[PDB]
Amino acid sequence: GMADKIAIVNMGSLFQQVAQKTGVSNTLENEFKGRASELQRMETDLQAKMKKLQSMKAGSDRTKLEKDVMAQRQTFAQKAQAFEQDRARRSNEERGKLVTRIQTAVKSVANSQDIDLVVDANAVAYNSSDVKDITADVLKQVK
Amino acid sequence: GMADKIAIVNMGSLFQQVAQKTGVSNTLERARRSNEERGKLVTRIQTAVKSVANSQDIDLVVDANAVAYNSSDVKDITADVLKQVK
Amino acid sequence: KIAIVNMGSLFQQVAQKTGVSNTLENEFKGRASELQRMETDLQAKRQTFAQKAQAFEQDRARRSNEERGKLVTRIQTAVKSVANSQDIDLVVDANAVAYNSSDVKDITADVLKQVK
């Protein structure tokens, strides 16, 4: 009865395995590597200016560098904010695409085997051996 | 046998809707109160879940968060529970 | 056929009884103090600090996960023992359950008695 209609699937494991196979994490790293280096250089160069702007006597040159530094800082902030946001957004968009593809596979396997309910293994403390763990069947079906 | 004796409910969705409707957030104007109001809504939602479960003769109601997939043969009583919340 | 068990509750009680938490503090208090003072020593004035305080952070998290995992394993062993004695075929974590009738037994107490 129950061995026929209920199954369990390890969503966490599918996610990890599919993420690695697709290389989603490395692909995101590549997508932001450039902007990340740029932002890093900006801070290196911005500290160097503050370094002098901390040891200069009042006057035309100090007033010009300050106005300059204060200008860079605002740009850095406005650029670093947009960075972190896009990072998080893109990351979420990707992890979500992964979840969806996995769920499509769970549904397919479930319909193939006439299973009405598939519970996430993380919420199961124990199951008899005639209750199917369809994780492996699902992985193979992920497109 | 536990077949149509199992149903699903989306606690996340319910907690959000009931929270907005009771405007518990705006009722701020911080842990002993944000967590207390959280609990208060959970108890109210669980009471409604229990009433709907008995009403439809369900023995076990699972949180949709722990369900990877359910066919149309497994009822989602979320909408029914929302109507019963008080 | 189906039962529920409060995994969170069991984990709390078993961790408390084994004292895993204090054992982990002891495991890291030394290296931790070496860092606290090592901080004020540098703060009162650094590539070795950051590169050492980082490894420490990792080691602790890794070690905490291991001890956590060992506790979960011991509890799962007790859940199975109780499930097989009472002919239960599926045990769901109570934290994923919004309602259960009396025919769906909560075996938390029975499991606790069998841990280890």
Image: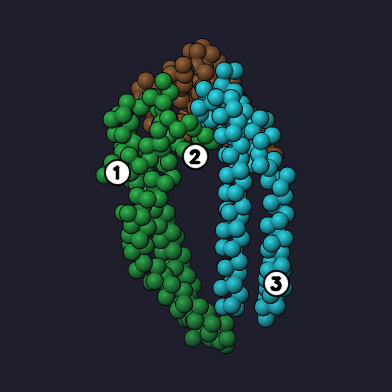
Chain colours: A green, B brown, C cyan
Write down the residue under mark 3: C34
**Quadrant (top left, top right, bottom left, bottom right) of the N terminus of chain A:** top left
Question: What's the residue at 68%, 68% (across, down)?
Answer: C31
Assess whether mark 3 and mark 1 are in contact (beta carbons under 8 angstroms): no
Identity, as a three-letter code, of the amino acid under mark 2? Asn
Kindly indicate whether the residues beneath marks 2 and 3 are on one polypeptide chain: no
Residue A52's place in the image compared with A17, above or below, is below
Q: Secondary structure at mark 1?
A: helix
Judging depth in this view, the residue of C14 and B66 nearest the camera is: C14
Question: How many residues crowd around disc 2 within 10 Å: few (fewer than 14), some, or many (20 or more)?
Answer: some
| Figure quadrant of residue C111 | top right
Question: How many residues crowd around disc 3 within 10 Å: few (fewer than 14), some, or many (20 or more)?
Answer: few
The dot on residue A122 is 2
* Residue A71 appears in the rendering: no
The dot on residue B57 is none
Question: What's the residue at 47%, 21% (across, down)?
Answer: B6
* Residue B60 appears in the rendering: yes
